[PDB]
Amino acid sequence: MPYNLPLPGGVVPRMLITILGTVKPNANRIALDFQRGNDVAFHFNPRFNENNRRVIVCNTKLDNNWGREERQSVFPFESGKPFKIQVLVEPDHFKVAVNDAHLLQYNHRVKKLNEISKLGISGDIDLTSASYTMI
């Protein structure tokens, strides 16, 4: 359920990425994957139903293996509703806000941000736009 947003020059501090769209009806998941070669530097994964609980799972994949998951229960998404995801890149973490409200922070595990060349956007959503700017 994939679209790739190329990031020429890679990820860099002050980069602000915005993803606008609408969650599909009866959604099961959404996923944003910042990729560095074969690795996934930052996986942002809202799960609409994990054992009857909503949860946002964040993680990193190195050497074909997922690491320690960071889980957040605050879940602002809703099936059939429009959403806005903003990811602000800082030197020490990815700062994520949904619908103009801070949601979570993910400390960098993959350190060479310049090598993170693209953001994969997938899941049960109708993607309107994916873009970025420098603040």
Image: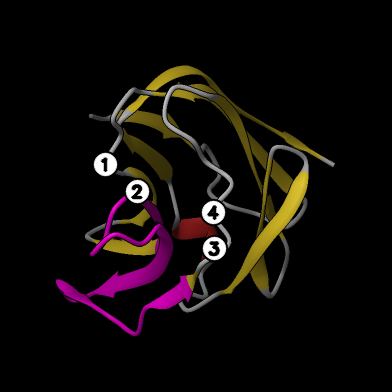
Q: CA distance from mark 2 to mark 4?
A: 9 Å
For residue 20, which numbered disc appears in the image? Answer: none
The percent coordinates of residue 124 (x first, y second) are: 30, 31
The percent coordinates of residue 114 (x first, y second) are: 54, 58
- Magenta highlight range: 42-71
For residue 48, which numbered disc appears in the image? Answer: 2
Task: Say what amino acid the circle numbered 1 marks.
Answer: Asn
Circle 1 Cα neighbour tier, 10 Å, few/some/many (<14 / 14–19 / ≥20) = some
> Do the residues under discs 2 and 4 have CB atoms within 8 angstroms?
no
State which mark lies toward you, 1 or 3.
1
Q: Nearer the viewer, residue 127 or 74?
A: 74
Task: Say what amino acid the circle numbered 2 marks.
Answer: Phe
The percent coordinates of residue 66 (x first, y second) are: 23, 75
For residue 113, which numbered disc appears in the image? Answer: 3
- Residue 17 appears in which quarter of the rendering? top right
> Do the residues under discs 2 and 1 have CB atoms within 8 angstroms?
yes
> Do the residues under discs 4 and 3 have CB atoms within 8 angstroms?
no
Task: Please name the residue shown 22% across and 60% down the image.
Answer: 38
- Residue 70 appears in which quarter of the rendering? bottom left
- What secondary structure is found at the residue carrying circle 4? loop
Q: Is residue 20 left or right of residue 126?
A: right
Q: CA distance from mark 4 to mark 3?
A: 27 Å
